[PDB]
Image (cartoon, helix red, strand yellow):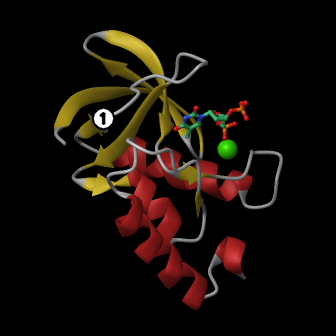
Amino acid sequence: LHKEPATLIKAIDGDTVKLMYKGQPMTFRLLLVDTPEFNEKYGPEASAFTKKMAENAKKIEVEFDKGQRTDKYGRGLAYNYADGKMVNEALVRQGLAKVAYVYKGNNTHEQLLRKAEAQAKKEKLNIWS
Ligand SMILES: Cc1cn([C@H]2C[C@H](OP(=O)(O)O)[C@@H](COP(=O)(O)O)O2)c(=O)[nH]c1=O
Ligand SMILES: [Ca+2]
């Protein structure tokens, strides 16, 4: 896989963000994760976490997997990086997302993310508390 440039247009919530990619505005949905909706417990905290990570970044990147690049709602499906740190992994490691939506052929980072999840569960963080 390879990282490609993007810029932040606006934070949306824990697992979606509006980015400019190839010069066009798109909503991205983070691969392999599920954050609570803003209305649910830890939803606001997941939102804040990804808003801060994206807004403080000097360099946002997206990385597509081998499979589908957009979902049925037209959202881009990617791993999102903020100054080299994967947002998808960081959410899972902090117990603010669960590993989820693992579809065959878009699952390159699955085991990385499951190892973070095991760590967050051991530490009893957030969703695992
Ligand atoms: C993360 C992900 C979600 N989706 C679709 C499955 C879910 O369909 P349904 O809307 O029919 O439940 C929805 C979950 O996204 P959200 O968690 O953002 O709601 O998005 C994909 O198709 N591919 C993906 O990789
Ligand atoms: Ca969600």
Residue 70, how many percent across, how many down? 46, 22
Q: Quadrant of the N terminus?
A: top left
Horizontal side of 46 relative to 52 (left or right) equals right
Residue farthest toward the top in the current orientation of the protein? 24
Horizontal side of 83 relative to 29 (left or right) equals left
Horizontal side of 90 relative to 85 (left or right) equals right
Residue 9, how many percent across, how many down? 43, 23
Mark 1 belongs to which amino acid? Phe
Residue farthest toward the front in the current orientation of the protein? 104
Query: Tag count in the figure?
Result: 1
Residue 34, how many percent across, how many down? 62, 51
Q: In this view, does 97 lie above or below 108?
A: below
- Locate residue 116: give its quadrant: bottom left
Q: Is residue 129 above or below residue 31?
A: below
| Residue nearer the viewer, 19 or 74 | 74
Instruction: Name the residue: 50% across, 61% down.
Output: 91
Q: Is residue 61 above or below residue 18?
A: below
Instruction: Name the residue: 22% across, 53% down.
Output: 84
Residue 74, how many percent across, how many down? 53, 16
Q: Does the residue labelled 1 lie within 8 Å of ligand 1?
A: no
| Residue nearer the viewer, 33 or 106 | 106
Residue farthest toward the bottom in the current orientation of the protein? 122
> What residue is shown with label 1?
64
| Residue nearer the viewer, 66 or 87 | 66
Q: Is residue 124 above or below residue 43?
A: below
Mark 1 closeness class: few <14, some 14–19, many ≥20 residues within 10 Å: many
Q: In which quarter of the image is ligand 2?
A: top right
Instruction: Name the residue: 43% across, 63% down.
Output: 90
